Image (cartoon, rainbow over all chains, first blue to last red; front, side, top):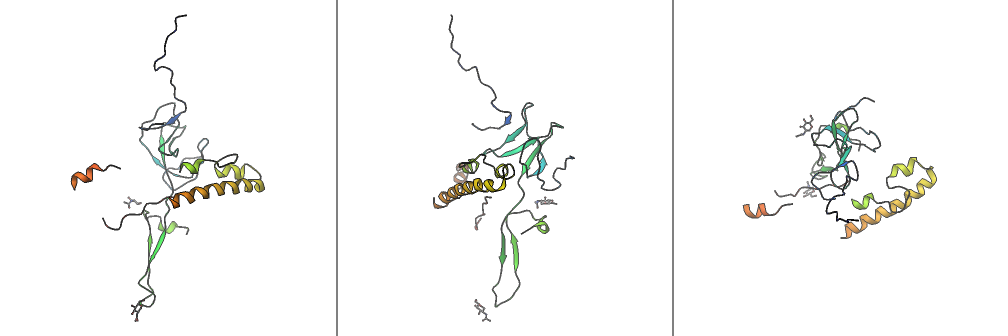
Length: 24
Length: 96
Length: 48
Length: 20
Ligand SMILES: *[C@@H]1O[C@H](CO)[C@@H](O)[C@H](O)[C@H]1NC(C)=O
Ligand SMILES: *[C@@H]1O[C@H](CO)[C@@H](O)[C@H](O)[C@H]1NC(C)=O
């Protein structure tokens, strides 16, 4: 069925929170 | 309710928040779909009002410890008072 | 501070919900347990 | 001292040291 690998696509903002220059 | 910003510390509820902080004008860049921002330790520092793109900072109301200076009982009875770590334009508005 | 946010065994973490949003007496019971937890956190910090 | 001073990059209160 022509499988494919998804490299780094599939990420979304989990919350409407604003965070600046941090790792969470 | 009308909005009073920086007049004095004022407890509040914008949409679903505990509040209890003084409000000030902010200039932080802020995305459209976002609503509020937490600086560090999940503490909410800035919020956005629905009536404008105007964002507001939050600062806790000042507190500190009062200390007493004294030259000793037998020498004299004057003292001096030091309110620690606080801008003092609110000294007459100190409850304790 | 992280320890401040946790609930230590209760319906909610922040005090005001337990206070106003339940009856006073058993709200007092939930308050009692949450107090014991926060006191323990202060204990370990000072000793370290 | 200038080099040493630059290399080191860093209900709660923090009191100030007594000697500046
Ligand atoms: C007052 O007390 C201080 C120490 O507490 C002492 O040095 C001083 O001599 C006393 N004053 C008099 C007049 O004795
Ligand atoms: C303290 O508060 C007064 C309010 O008039 C303000 O003018 C001053 O800039 C504040 N900070 C300082 C530096 O004292």
